Amino acid sequence: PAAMFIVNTNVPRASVPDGFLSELTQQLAQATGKPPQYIAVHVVPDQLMAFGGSSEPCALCSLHSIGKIGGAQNRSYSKLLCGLLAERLRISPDRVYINYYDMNAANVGWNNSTFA
Amino acid sequence: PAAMFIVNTNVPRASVPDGFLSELTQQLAQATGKPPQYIAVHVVPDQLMAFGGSSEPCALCSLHSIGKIGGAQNRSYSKLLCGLLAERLRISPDRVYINYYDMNAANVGWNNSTFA
Amino acid sequence: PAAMFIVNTNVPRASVPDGFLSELTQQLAQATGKPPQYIAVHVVPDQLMAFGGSSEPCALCSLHSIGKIGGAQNRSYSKLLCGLLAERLRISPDRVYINYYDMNAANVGWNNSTFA
Ligand SMILES: CC(C)c1nn2ccccc2c1C(=O)[C@@H](C)N
Ligand SMILES: [Cl-]
Ligand SMILES: [Cl-]
Ligand SMILES: [Cl-]
Ligand SMILES: [Cl-]
Ligand SMILES: [Cl-]
Ligand SMILES: [Cl-]
Ligand SMILES: [Cl-]
Ligand SMILES: [Cl-]
Ligand SMILES: [Cl-]
Ligand SMILES: [Cl-]
Ligand SMILES: [Cl-]
C-alpha cells in the first residue's frame, strides 16, 4: 500500500518551513487513505529549473501510489498539493506540475520483497 | 499539453551554461510543436553516476509529455537531445539514456487540478 | 537491453563507500543478465526525506529496464538491493522502496535513436 511523493523546486532550502516533511506525510496519508507508516516524502530544494522559460519559483513533483489514483482522486490531490506548495513555499499553482503514477504492487519492492 | 524534461548528469554545475535551460525549453517547444510556456526543464548537475561502469561524463534523462510521444517522434527527440547534451555539456551521445513517457492528461496535475 | 538504477537516500555522502557504484553495476549486471556496458547507476545522498514520517535512514529507488522485470524477478531484485543498502549504507530494508519499470524499447533513447 505504499505511496511516495517527491517535490523538486528552485526555492531555496531555507525557505522550506520546519515540519514541511511531516505535514506532507500527514496530509497525504489522509488524502490517500493509507497509514502514514507507508507514506514516503522527498523534498529537493535549490534546483536548477525553469517553467515556461521563466526561472521564477516553480515545482515538478510526482506521486507514485499503489492504487488510489484516478481522475477525480488526482484532481483532489492536485488541489491539496498545489495549495500546500503555494502556502508553504510561495510557489504559484500555475508553476507546478505533478505527475501521478498508479503502481502495481508487484512492481514495488520493500523489506527484501515486493508487495505482490 | 504540458511537457517536461529532466537531465541528471555528473558534469559539474559550473560546466552547465547559464542559457541551457532556455535553450532546451525553446528547442523542445519547436520539436513537440508546443508553445514554450508549456515546457518545464530541470537540470541536475554534480551527480554521483556511472554509465557502463565508467564515471566519464554521462546523462540519464526523462521526457514526460501529454502527447507528442511515439516511436518515430522519440527517435527524432533523441537526436535533438543528444546534440544539445554533446555540444553544451560535452557528454558523448553513447553515454546518454532518455526515458520517454506519454502522460495521460488525467495523470498530470497543474494549477490546482489536472489537464483532464 | 538498457537498465538503470537510482537510489535516493538521506544517508550522508561520506557514508557511501568507495566502490559502491561499481558494486551496483556488477551486481545488477549479474541479476538482470545484461552486460555491464548497458547498466547505468545513480546514487543521490544527503537528501531531505521521510519514510513513515521519520527521518531515520531510508531510501527511495527505481530500477528501469528493457525487459527482465516481473513478479518473481522483482522479488529477487528486492532481496539483492535491500541487502546491499543494508550492508553498505546501513539502511533498514523496511525503510526502502524500489519502484520497478519495464520500459518499451521505443521509449528508451540512446545515442541518437531508440532501442526499438
Ligand atoms: C558499443 C556497444 C557495445 C554498446 N554499448 N552500449 C551501451 C549502452 C546500450 C547499448 C550499447 C551497445 C550496443 O551494442 C547497442 C547496439 N545496443
Ligand atoms: Cl491503499
Ligand atoms: Cl521538515
Ligand atoms: Cl506498475
Ligand atoms: Cl491536454
Ligand atoms: Cl563496474
Ligand atoms: Cl571511471
Ligand atoms: Cl499516464
Ligand atoms: Cl559489457
Ligand atoms: Cl518474473
Ligand atoms: Cl537485509
Ligand atoms: Cl514504456
Image: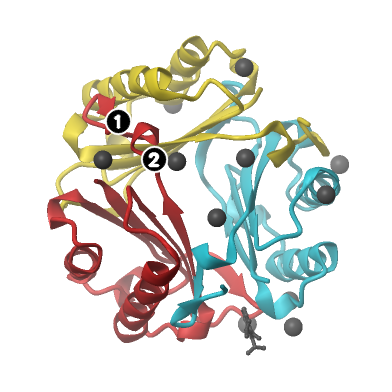
Chain colours: A yellow, B red, C cyan
Residue at 40% x, 34% y is B107
If the picture is divided into quarters, which one holds ligand 2?
top right
Question: Relative to the observer, which residue lies in front, C58 or A65?
Answer: A65
Question: Relative to the observer, which residue lies in front, B116 or A12?
Answer: B116
Q: Is mark 2 within 8 Å of ligand 8?
A: yes
Q: Is mark 1 within 8 Å of ligand 5?
A: yes
Residue B52 point in image, percent of width and height:
66, 78
How many residues crowd around disc 1 within 10 Å: few (fewer than 14), some, or many (20 or more)?
few
Tell me if residue A3 comes above or below residue A23 in the rendering: below
Residue at 57% x, 74% y is C115
Tell me if residue B33 comes above or below residue B112 in the rendering: below
Q: Which of the chains bears the disc numbered 1? A: B
**Residue beneath label 2, please?**
B104
Residue A53 visible:
no
Q: Which of the chains bears the disc numbered 2? A: B
Residue at 32% x, 77% y is B80
Q: Is residue B102 left or right of residue C16?
A: left
Quarter assignment of residue A15: top left
> Looking at the image, is mark 2 or mark 1 earlier in the sequence?
2
Secondary structure at numbered mark 2: loop
Residue C40 point in image, percent of width and height:
62, 69
Asked if the residue under mark 1 is in contact with the one under mark 2, i.e. CB atoms within 8 Å, the reply is yes
Residue B95 point in image, percent of width and height:
52, 80
Residue A102 point in image, percent of width and height:
55, 32
**The N terminus of chain A lies in which quarter of the figure?**
top right
How many residues crowd around disc 2 within 10 Å: few (fewer than 14), some, or many (20 or more)?
some
Quarter assignment of residue C99: top right
**Residue beneath label 1, please?**
B116
